[PDB]
Image (tube, rainbow, N blue to C red):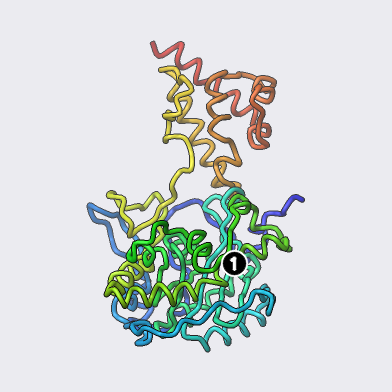
Amino acid sequence: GMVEKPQLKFKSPIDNSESHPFIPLLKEKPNALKPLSESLRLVDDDENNPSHYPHPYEYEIDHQEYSPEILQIREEIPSKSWDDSVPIWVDTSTELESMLEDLKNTKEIAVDLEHHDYRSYYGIVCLMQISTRERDYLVDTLKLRENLHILNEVFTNPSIVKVFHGAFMDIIWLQRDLGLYVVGLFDTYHASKAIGLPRHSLAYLLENFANFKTSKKYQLADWRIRPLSKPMTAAARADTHFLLNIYDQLRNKLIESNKLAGVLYESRNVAKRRFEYSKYRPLTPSSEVYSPIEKESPWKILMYQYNIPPEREVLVRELYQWRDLIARRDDESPRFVMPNQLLAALVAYTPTDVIGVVSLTNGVTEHVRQNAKLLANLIRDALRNIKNTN
């Protein structure tokens, strides 16, 4: 296939300029203890962290109490038989409405998401998986990107527990893309750790409590593809299908060992995590704020020292900044535009014409090929400056 970029269909064009701190997409704030007003404003500069907007549901996450039945040991409810139902595909506004109506009638729900970042600059949430005790929902977050915010009614209802496994990034992705927030989170990863299970992954939990073997044969998959393949649909369904039962067992064990308070504490902090552009990231990197983390070569002269000659660091950096600006412009990831190995290859062979750039023994990307002359000029300039400097 080709998988047309789903962004070209967003009702609101992505902005990679980063000309101001992240602004919450939240227009309405249900289950509010503190009006949305006091929320959207700004926290002017400070030594530690520069100007930025605060987490809108930070207050309620701190003040609203947990449903009284989360503190009680209860008979656990086994996961529903996989074959007794099909996952419910939701990519319509009316289907989204009905699901919401269904989610409002629960005491707890299991949630997970599928993310894509190869063909997007910051990344995009491609799917949302939601399970109630009765059914599994698969939500098209590309097609309903603009509507999803209506889930805050349930996602921020402290009366409904939201169960996630290691939601540190989901929380980030949720606000950043759908303007969704979570109040009443229960993180099974933090629960696994508190109880002290040998391993703490979702896969480990599924294998031992749900006798379900998982396959990471999709952790490198393209969740943008419509329709979803059966095996991919099944794998997504498995992320939440068994989670509430695992929640029951972990929750009870926590109560039994008097460690629930800590898990709930950890979870509120995960839910409090705030997403901000690297441009406005706090000076001291903490687990309270998430800023994009280059999935590649050590900023500028990479430590992957392909024997990076001395004088050639300016060239290396210009290539980095060029790659980043193009990535932001076309809303692509730096690696799609030019992987480090190619950037390195360019720095190593320093081709100075189009032929040299495109025939790089290493192979070349579309961006590099379409900008071969610009890159050849950039490289010719870098060399000339060297032979000149000293």
Left or right of 278 on screen, residue 154: right
Q: Position of residue 359 (x, y in %)?
A: 69, 22
**Crowding at mark 1 (Cα within 10 Å: few <14, some 14-19, many 20+):** many
Task: Look at the picture and state if 263 lies above or below 2.
Answer: below
Task: Look at the picture and state if 294 lies above or below 345.
Answer: below
Residue linked to disc 1: 238
Q: Quadrant of the C terminus?
A: top left
Q: Can see residue 30?
A: no
Which residue is at the front of the view, 99 or 141? 99
Which residue is at the front of the view, 385 or 57? 57
Q: Residue at x 34, y 66 (%)?
A: 195
Q: In which quarter of the view is residue 89 placed? A: bottom right
Q: Amino acid at mark 1?
A: Ala
Q: Position of residue 87 (x, y in %)?
A: 66, 74
Task: Look at the picture and state if 104 lies above or below 346.
Answer: below
Left or right of 330 on screen, residue 264: left
Q: Residue at x 58, y 70 (%)?
A: 129
Q: Residue at x 33, y 70 (%)?
A: 263
Instruction: Give SS at disc 1.
Output: helix
- Of all residues, the one furthest to the right in this rendering is 1
Q: Position of residue 228 (x, y in %)?
A: 71, 62
Left or right of 49 on screen, residue 325: right
Q: Residue at x 55, y 41 (%)?
A: 334
